[PDB]
Amino acid sequence: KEMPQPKTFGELKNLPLLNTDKPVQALMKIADELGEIFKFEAPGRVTRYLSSQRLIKEACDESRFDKNLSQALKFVRDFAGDGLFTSWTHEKNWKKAHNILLPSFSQQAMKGYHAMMVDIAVQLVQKWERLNADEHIEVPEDMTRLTLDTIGLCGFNYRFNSFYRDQPHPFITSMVRALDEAMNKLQRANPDDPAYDENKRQFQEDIKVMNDLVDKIIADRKASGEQSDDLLTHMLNGKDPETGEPLDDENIRYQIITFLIAGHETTSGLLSFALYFLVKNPHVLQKAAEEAARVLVDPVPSYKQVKQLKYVGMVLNEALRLWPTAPAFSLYAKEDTVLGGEYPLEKGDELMVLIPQLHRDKTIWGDDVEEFRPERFENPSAIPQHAFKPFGNGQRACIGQQFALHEATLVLGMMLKHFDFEDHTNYELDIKETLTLKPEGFVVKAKSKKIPL
Ligand code: HEM
Ligand SMILES: O=C(O)[C@H](Cc1ccccc1)NC(=O)[C@@H]1CCCN1C(=O)OCc1ccccc1
Ligand SMILES: N[C@H]1CCCc2ccccc21
């Protein structure tokens, strides 16, 4: 089997196809044209983009394939270091931190974070309750204020107070500008041109701001002796059951930077796409709003009431089906192997999983793959293995999955209990790409149902 390949630019091969603000959407269009697998070549590199459940189920075999750091992850590693997301599976600090942090992220741990999540969710509802007639909501802006504040308070008992300001925290200015520079460098065909010298100075200054501010939070907590039930305490106190070793202060810094990036870029996208799909599908909004009214019978939602929001959970999974907010992950072949009885790979060969194309595989989902239908997720047991992968694969899957879904279910539940929503501009979906996807310029009007907190 001779693999399809998209159009080429002489010595640059396929590299200029990623010279776009929307690289994942460009690759999705290539997938639609070429099918379940295509080769992508750059000077000094080759990867293969996978779109079918048939081939992705093989790529998800951990005995054959392991997590690869894509070029983007190698650039983020310059500030995220050997934190869980930018570490190789074979680095000592990956398994150590995984073993130490897994119990901090379990479904049972969510009982402990619930009160803090409610504190921030109530601030969002009170902001929207206090808007004047015909003012509107900047949805991804307010969802990012919420998710950043939530990880701040659950992560290290720190209040970013995002609802009190329009200008970001100094840590966040440097973090956003570092992420943008990392993503900007992917397309850069000539990195050493002194026209990029300024970008280079700004990056080193941003890395130094993040390192200095997180190193101070760690030193401050060690100085205070405070045992708050948060990730920083779990990381200062925890021993890996395997090595019997704790994490060192440098790695703790990288984990905090990692979790702050995740808290800014991830759940906020999911919540924005979920609200987009509800205002575009008013019958689906009615079903989710009915569930919220029937279930959330107290002014403060309980942990148990959030677990009871089955249809709200189905809405979130259907948003993740169409627009998985972390849309691609990279693997390498552990040994020589043959993919799908047709494509021979050598040890070291790279694969990319295109999660939005996986989630549109008609052999799995049927012919209506573009329709927003939460009822696809009524019965978890009816989804085949490796057909739905918004949180990645195996031991390198998302450690934050339970945290992300608990926060999103709680917040979306309270939003549907407290307000009616209007797509007052007839918003045209415009997907901005960083590491993650968000609907840029998505705005709505909310009308209070006047239910007290
Ligand atoms: C909608 C929300 C989220 C989605 C869709 C999501 C998706 C993913 C995906 C696809 C991966 C695998 C990456 C790869 O294979 O290269 C991943 C890994 C990870 N995610 Fe998330 N994530 C979300 C929220 C969060 C949150 C809230 C946190 C932390 C607060 C988090 C922390 C992580 C970490 C640390 C890893 C690396 C895990 C490891 O390799 O040990 N994520 N996530
Ligand atoms: O970063 C990469 O290597 C590739 C693009 C590429 C660049 C140069 C030659 C060949 C391919 N990246 C990707 O295909 C996707 C699309 C844009 C960024 N990206 C990616 O994987 O970002 C990192 C990431 C984000 C979210 C979750 C896991 C990993
Ligand atoms: N949740 C993952 C995937 C999305 C991007 C990202 C960034 C930092 C830390 C973790 C993650």
Image: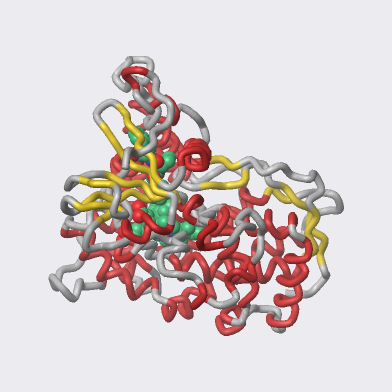
Q: Position of residue 316 (x, y in %)?
A: 59, 65
Residue furthest top in the image:
194
In front of the other: 207 or 307? 307
Does residue 66 appear to the left or right of 408 in the view shown? Answer: left
Does residue 194 appear to the left or right of 319 in the view shown? Answer: left
Identity of the residue drawn at 64% across and 71% down: 375
Q: Is residue 409 above or below residue 372?
A: below
Q: Position of residue 75 (x, y in %)?
A: 32, 38
Identity of the residue drawn at 40% across and 37% down: 178
> Quarter of the picture for ligand 2?
top left
Q: Position of residue 408 (x, y in %)?
A: 57, 65
* Label total for image: 0
Q: Is residue 85 above or below residue 43?
A: below
| Residue 57 found in image quarter | bottom left
Which corner quadrant holds the C terminus?
bottom right
Which corner quadrant holds the N terminus?
top left
Does residue 12 appear to the left or right of 168 in the view shown? Answer: left
In front of the other: 219 or 275? 275
Does residue 392 appear to the left or right of 308 in the view shown? Answer: left
Identity of the residue drawn at 17% across and 50% down: 336
**Can residue 35 be seen in this snapshot?**
yes
| Residue 222 found in image quarter | bottom left
In front of the other: 408 or 170? 408
**Can residue 328 be seen in this snapshot?**
no
Q: Is residue 208 above or below residue 355?
A: above
Identity of the residue drawn at 78% across and 65% down: 283
In front of the other: 82 or 115? 82
